[PDB]
Length: 71
Length: 71
Image (cartoon, rainbow over all chains, first blue to last red; front, side, top):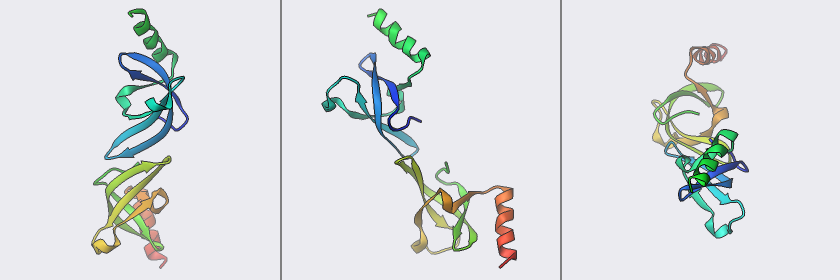
């Protein structure tokens, strides 16, 4: 699971954006994460589930790049 | 982390009692567990943190036994 302060990749629409986890919570055997999209307004901060996020690894950054290159 | 429905050992005072996890929640990087002590009044159902609980393993059951014998 993702930790508070952790930088991640996050979908917002079909592209991946760098984000930071502000809060992590689990109820009913499900994680939710309140994320801030880096360089975006705080108005876009929101709760998301695991399926919206990727660990900030070079492997997942390559996924970000592939999506950028295929437009 | 313990799961809903899981039987555990729980301190209530210095002895260990079998209990069941009713609900598990995590906030601020901390699990809490709402437990029912088996055979006890529902009045005693309560939220506890990890320090109050032990996995139902043979080693921890042996700890329960040791505490009973040193009573």
